[PDB]
């Protein structure tokens, strides 16, 4: 177009994205201030007005970005994320989910965008080890629920409660004073279940970490 | 044979192993559903029937696999594991040990098989460090049992209880509020035993991890 | 100058810096002894006299060092640190902040100076990951304060209290028995907030550590 | 000598060191059995006799080893350790220190000897970082003792008690529920002291570990 060139030369301009970055920061501090009961009584209307007069800017700039790249928008992870976080912020739990638009700042800022996509690119390698661990949790979740579910309903009564207690034991939070030692007052051989479980879960996780270290180092040694 | 070629051309076919994989998954979800008291009252007979009509399939397919490879079966770690997990599932604790046949899914799936055998191949290097640690635990288990066994019978009364408390201190779970600090109310110099113990156990474990990192990296730098 | 050469040939002499090192050590042991109520009653005056007759030496040697390097002093991180730790020790919380002049010993000793500046040079790389984590804490601090702030005021009532509880959960100290499990007595789905939070925070920190390992190894592989 | 060749050809023979290894193992199991009150009542005399008839063998074989290498013995770390652990076991706390002669098995066994000396060779590099950490603990031990020593005498009353509580906070055992959170009921800004302390102590330790990883990898990349 005649003006289509102008609008794609503003949408891809530095100052338009710098402006929506200042708005993300201002909204983030606004969102931060909205936890204060005293501030909300004193200036609640300026902030809620502000929150409206900023959600409108964000929605119009989503409209513009969609126009300049009609289908390129809906195949791009970052702009897709923007689409969804402005969608959440537009409906009349959702209240809390609205804060996620502050990750909008990870999208705009390129250095942050680089770090995030680096972290994502790590994941494909871990898929194989995660699958063994999820299967491993599934198997020991079922064993623990059938062994301790009656006498210890709060911790091992349900499969979900046993995926919870086992995750806590793997994080090694009160694994012994909190869970195993109380269990051994009724069932005196519970260590056979947990100390092996601990050992396996640690080993795998260690290897997971070492795996991440050689997949990173390969591109350097070449 | 005439049909022996047919049976070895089905046993090594893709679809026969895909079929026993679907059966492992169906049995795994069945086993998962058997923790629900409500589901077991409503559909317990369909599932127990299912569990029988699947343990039979698994046993016949073990029979077939043994026939096609008569001695190759009993020298192969994965099929040996299958032999034993279908054996456990065939006897009239065992109830819980039956769930282990879900690791049958690690055997069938090749990508999982790769990850598991990678994890195994790590272990030979750790044998030397594990032996020093097991000897180290043995020595400090005996010291702790003789020092605190009377006044603190629940934690250090027996060698096994002291291999337990020392493992908890090495995992650093309530090492200080839970065990050392109570001990210092009777025996005020217990830190000499534990803080050195902590230090040694951490150092060795750190080296263990670093060891795993150079044994992995060697095949890349070549 | 005529004597300016003499004073710059003492200020940069080995024995002048060896002397102020002995004074740092003597003051450090003095500072160590000043916690003892009994020693302070018995020899408090010798030590406070000593503390004065040493703060004067340190101040004159700051004066000398400033003279020999007039502007080189105020552009040098180590001597700048000396300026500020002798300033703190000169005013008529400050009492406790005075102990920081024992890090004066890191400045004088060159091997220590090397280690410290190595540790500093690591930091620039972590700036990108720290910024994502600080933003991530900010977002989940706000979510946690709005979700649990009323029913759990002590832990999540304020943004600062939620940056505190979330840091404790990331350190994995009583994350489950101490915070999540009590929360699930009122709000039974709190794991959705924390177990994801845990996962993200661990992953990032792991990568942070792996990052530090490849930035160190690069100068070796070249 | 005429027989001196014979005795140095037995002392350095495989079977003499294999024999004292069997004696270390037999004594280790004996020492293990001596925790059992029931076994000591039933067979206490056979074991104490055994313990004497083995401490004598060990002492004569120390005598022989000293003779074959008169001064080479007292300049060799492993045999020096043997000298001292047979000395401890010869005097008429010492009772518990006697168990250390089971590390005699690390000395005899060469693969174990290799692992141990590898672990030792790591340490020289950590000396610089350990010195910064020990100075760092000293400084924050003094700060914590002067800030919280009166209101919290059990944890921070003495410098030793503050080197204890700070070590526990660095191990991250009940750092927050156990120590900081109780402190903030009297002194509401204690996080300024501990969360910075935590951060520094973690960072340094991380670098310590990364250091160990590049000092190991250097001999491989060459
Ligand atoms: C990225 C990280 C940057 C740094 C983040 C800084 C976070 C600091 C938060 C700590 C503030 C809370 C401390 C405090 O005491 O403030 C009180 C209020 C809540 O208490 P309040 O509601 O005032 O008490 C009511 C009493 N009543 C019921 C009897 C009437 O609580 C507040 O006033 C909250 C104050 C809002 C702080 C917002 C700071 C935003 C930093 C900029 C980050 C932008 C990133 C895009
Ligand atoms: C930390 C704050 C998070 C905030 C919420 C985020 C929500 C999603 C936002 C997505 C924005 C980032 C997307 C992204 O960076 O993708 C790029 C990555 C890395 O690229 P990379 O792998 O380097 O590309 C090389 C491959 N090539 C050349 C053939 C194209 O390419 C890949 O994706 C590799 C494939 C692995 C994908 C695994 C992703 C899912 C893990 C977490 C799922 C959470 C669900 C709730
Ligand atoms: C590829 C990207 C990376 C993703 C990797 C993470 C995989 C996530 C695993 C979770 C999959 C299974 C989820 C699940 O089973 O949820 C069950 C429970 C819910 O408890 P629930 O029974 O609903 O409580 C209700 C109480 N009631 C009925 C009395 C009112 O909720 C829980 O307990 C979940 C606790 C977390 C357990 C994590 C277990 C496997 C993690 C493997 C980690 C891999 C790296 C090592
Ligand atoms: C590999 C990991 C994949 C993802 C795993 C998903 C795990 C999800 C488990 C969480 C389900 C439990 C939550 C829940 O509230 O369910 C209730 C039942 C047990 O309570 P219920 O017996 O219904 O209560 C009785 C009350 N009474 C005594 C008064 C009559 O508990 C149940 O109903 C259990 C529901 C069965 C879930 C099975 C999911 C299998 C996922 C597929 C994995 C296949 C791997 C090969
Ligand atoms: C090569 C493949 C890797 C394998 C490495 C793992 C080595 C496993 C070490 C276990 C060896 C010794 C086993 C043992 O001594 O068992 C004793 C206790 C049993 O307690 P017990 O006294 O039966 O309780 C009965 C209570 N009663 C009589 C009043 C009714 O049970 C326990 O306390 C065991 C607790 C675990 C302690 C682990 C100690 C050494 C681990 C070294 C780890 C190496 C990597 C760092
Ligand atoms: C770099 C690290 C080097 C090694 C650091 C060594 C730290 C050792 C500290 C442990 C000392 C405390 C143990 C102890 O029981 O001493 C008691 C005094 C405090 O109790 P006290 O005030 O005597 O009790 C009064 C009783 N009342 C109220 C009824 C009259 O507490 C004291 O007497 C404190 C003793 C001062 C020890 C100063 C050691 C400095 C080591 C040199 C480091 C120089 C680095 C530049
Ligand atoms: C580039 C060099 C490295 C630096 C990296 C570290 C970044 C430090 C993050 C701290 C920034 C935000 C500070 C902040 O928000 O302070 C709030 C609270 C204070 O609590 P407050 O509400 O004042 O308590 C008063 C109680 N009252 C009113 C009732 C009397 O105090 C806290 O809760 C702070 C707790 C620490 C939280 C740390 C959170 C982000 C850390 C990211 C770590 C990066 C590496 C993974
Ligand atoms: C290197 C690691 C190898 C594997 C280490 C194996 C450790 C196993 C230790 C667990 C044994 C303790 C379990 C148990 O219930 O035994 C009971 C006794 C102590 O109770 P007891 O004194 O029998 O009870 C008296 C009751 N009363 C007062 C009313 C009369 O406690 C005992 O009977 C202790 C049994 C001695 C076990 C010695 C095993 C040595 C393994 C070989 C290692 C050699 C390395 C050089
Ligand atoms: C784990 C069970 C322990 C049981 C108690 C042990 C008590 C002491 C037993 C001593 C036996 C081992 C002695 C030893 O292996 O020394 C050899 C190490 C490693 O040799 P390496 O550095 O490879 O030699 C190369 C240097 N070269 C070619 C120029 C000679 O050469 C070095 O020593 C390097 C120098 C660093 C020494 C740091 C040692 C002290 C750390 C722990 C102190 C604890 C005191 C209670
Ligand atoms: C080169 C080979 C590696 C060696 C590195 C390890 C360095 C060891 C540091 C210990 C140096 C200072 C020792 C010290 O100050 O001892 C004080 C306390 C003793 O408490 P105390 O006051 O005697 O309790 C008596 C109670 N009473 C009077 C009421 C009856 O005892 C404690 O609290 C000690 C707790 C351990 C603290 C460790 C602090 C610095 C560790 C730096 C670690 C470096 C790697 C990161
Ligand atoms: C990109 C990533 C790793 C790439 C790599 O490091 N090397 C591969 C290239 C050489 C890819 C390549 C192959 C992928 C696995 C399998 O396909 C399917 C498999 C099925 C299991 O039930 C659970 C998922 C499994 C383990 C997958 C995980 C992950 O998705 C892998 C490892
Ligand atoms: C394959 C594995 C490591 C291979 C490697 O990294 N380098 C070896 C090849 C060069 C092998 C090679 C040598 C093996 C040790 C000894 O034989 C026996 C020894 C007796 C002890 O009391 C306890 C077990 C010990 C430590 C064994 C551990 C482990 O089984 C080792 C390290
Ligand atoms: C020296 C350090 C890393 C050097 C490196 O490893 N490679 C860079 C050279 C190739 C430098 C180079 C680029 C720097 C970042 C950006 O400039 C600004 C950015 C803004 C964010 O909102 C928060 C800070 C960010 C992430 C900075 C972090 C840090 O300060 C970086 C990574
Ligand atoms: C062998 C070990 C490291 C070897 C290395 O990695 N590179 C050195 C060779 C190149 C050696 C070489 C130099 C040694 C330090 C200093 O001499 C004294 C110094 C005084 C402090 O107050 C406290 C101890 C310090 C930090 C020592 C630590 C350690 O003893 C070091 C690092
Ligand atoms: Na804990
Ligand atoms: Na912990």
Image: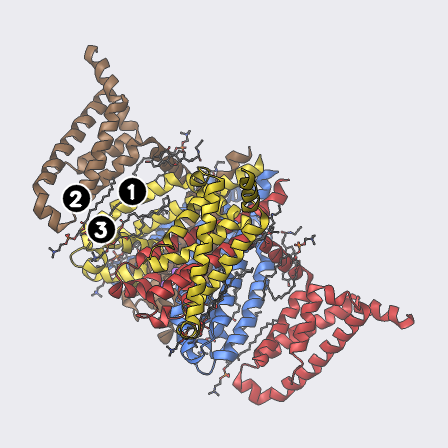
Chain colours: A brown, B blue, C yellow, D red
Q: In which quarter of the image is residue B130?
A: bottom right
Check residue A94 in the rendering and tell me which mark sits there, or answer none.
2
Q: In which quarter of the image is the C terminus of chain A?
A: top right
Q: What element does badge 3 sit on?
A: helix
Could you tell whether D197 is left or right of B74 in the image?
left
Rendered residue at 18%/38% (across/down): A88
Q: Does mark 3 have its CB less than 8 Å from ligand 1?
A: yes
Q: Marks 2 and 3: which is nearer the front?
A: 3
User: As displayed, is residue D51 above or below residue D79?
Assistant: below
Number of other residues with Cα within 10 Å of mark 2, as a class: few under 14, some 14 to 19, many 20 or more: few
Disc 2 to disc 3, C-alpha distance: 19 Å
Q: Residue at x 73, y 64 (%)?
A: D75
Q: Nearer the viewer, residue B110 or C1?
A: C1
Q: Which mark is residue C135?
A: 1
Residue highlighted by disc 3: C159
Observer-nearest residue: D141 or A41? Answer: D141
Within 8 Å of ligand 2, the CB of disc 2? no
Q: Quadrant of residue D7?
A: bottom right
Where is residue A170? Give x, y as percent.
39, 58
Cα separation, mark 2 vs mark 1, equals 20 Å
Residue at 27% across, 21% down: A12
Question: In the drawing, does residue D159 fall left or right of residue D89?
Answer: left
Chain at numbered mark 2: A
């Amino acid at each position: 177009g005649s003006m289509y060139l102008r609008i794609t030369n503003i949408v891809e301009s530095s100052f338009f994205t710098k402006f929506i970055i200042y708005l993300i920061v201002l909204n983030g501090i606004t969102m931060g201030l909205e936890t204060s009961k005293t501030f909300m009584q004193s200036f609640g209307v300026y902030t809620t007005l502000f929150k409206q007069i900023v959600i409108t800017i964000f929605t119009i700039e989503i409209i513009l970005r969609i126009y300049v790249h009609r289908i390129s928008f809906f195949k791009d992870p970052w702009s897709l994320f923007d689409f969804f976080v402005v969608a959440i912020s537009l409906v009349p739990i959702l209240r809390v989910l609205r804060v996620l638009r502050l990750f909008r700042l990870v999208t705009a800022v390129p250095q942050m965008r680089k770090i995030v996509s680096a972290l994502i690119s790590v994941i494909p390698g871990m898929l194989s080890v995660i699958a063994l661990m999820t299967l491993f949790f599934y198997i020991f979740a079922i064993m623990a629920t059938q062994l301790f579910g009656e006498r210890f309903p709060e911790w091992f009564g349900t499969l979900g409660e046993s995926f919870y207690t086992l995750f806590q034991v793997m994080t090694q939070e009160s694994w012994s004073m909190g869970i195993v030692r109380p269990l051994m007052e009724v069932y005196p051989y519970a260590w056979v279940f947990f100390i092996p479980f601990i050992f396996v879960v640690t080993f795998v996780m260690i290897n997971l970490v070492v795996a991440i270290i050689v997949d990173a180092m390969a591109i350097l040694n070449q």
